[PDB]
Length: 103
Image (cartoon, rainbow, N blue to C red; front, side, top):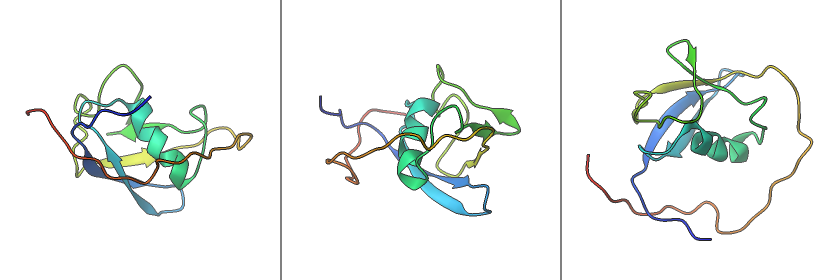
């Protein structure tokens, strides 16, 4: 199916190699949507990919806006296990879409 055009802001995330990677996630989207973009950056599974906020890990159910994660929020990715036993390849990627809704 297609994707509906909704709000989307840019955030700052830090890696284990002291490298900051730029990511984009909707204000209503959840952590599940965030890692989705990370797959293109490093390409790691959810069991190994975990988001941290204010020292507290993040999980699904809630949205970025609920985690006080703004366009200037600092995210951290911590890995516990190892995977890299999968692949990822599909068109219609790397495309910027418009926004909508109120705040």
